[PDB]
Image: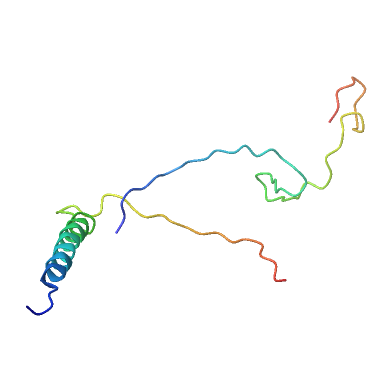
């Protein structure tokens, strides 16, 4: 009877597999490719300036 | 890379003030120097101001 952390490896593999499934689904439906027509909108984001003192 | 876009239009109303550029159709430009009241105007003999 030596020491044992097989349940630790199973738990860590379960965490890795569940996180890989969720992140694969999110990176599947957020960086998809639009088809035959192109990007149907535009980003249009612009940043203006401010008056920032320097004390 | 983008999830959703919100587009917001705005509308604003600009009156006139000393500094704007008005000009006829014959090439005679100008910047509005002062903005006088009514009673400091040259009126004719009938009373109507200019």
Which residue ends up furthest to the top in the rendered image?
B46
Residue shown at the point (41%, 54%) measured from the top left = A44
Q: Which color mode does the image show?
A: rainbow
Quarter of the view holding residue A18? bottom left
B5 left or right of A52 in image:
left
Of A19 and B37, the residue lying toward us = A19
Quadrant into which the C terminus of chain A falls: bottom right
In the rendered image of this protein, does residue A46 appear above or below residue B4?
below
Residue shown at the point (14%, 54%) measured from the top left = A36
Of B47 and A42, the residue lying toward us = A42
Image coords of residue B3 (percent x, y): 31, 51
Quadrant into which the N terminus of chain A falls: bottom left
Residue shown at the point (90%, 26%) measured from the top left = B44
Of B4 and A39, the residue lying toward us = B4
Quarter of the view holding residue A39? bottom left
Image coords of residue B24 (percent x, y): 68, 44
């Amino acid at each position: 009877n030596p020491i044992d952390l097989t349940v630790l490896a199973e738990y860590h593999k379960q965490i890795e597999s569940n996180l890989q499934r969720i992140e694969r689904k999110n990176q599947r439906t957020w960086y998809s490719k639009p088809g035959e027509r192109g990007i149907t909108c535009s980003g249009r984001q612009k940043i203006k300036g401010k008056s920032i003192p320097l004390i | 890379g983008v999830l959703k876009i919100v587009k917001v239009y705005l509308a604003v109303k600009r009156r006139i003030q000393p500094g704007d550029k008005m000009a006829g159709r014959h090439g005679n430009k100008g910047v509005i120097s002062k903005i006088n009241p009514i009673e400091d105007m040259p009126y004719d003999e009938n009373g109507t101001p200019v």
